[PDB]
Image (cartoon, rainbow, N blue to C red):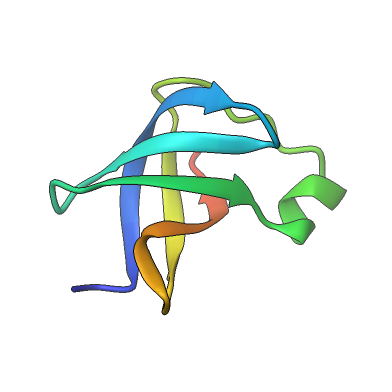
Length: 68
């Protein structure tokens, strides 16, 4: 039930979405945040990310950080 969770990127999807596996065992789809878009942060499969999940749907969220 955590709302801020780390995961690994599985694959890019259209509309700037990514399939992610979280470290609580759940799959989610997320896009990068506006701040990350502004800073042109590349996301690739196998990257480690922090996701803020949607209150309305814990299977959707926003990527807010990608580990270097």
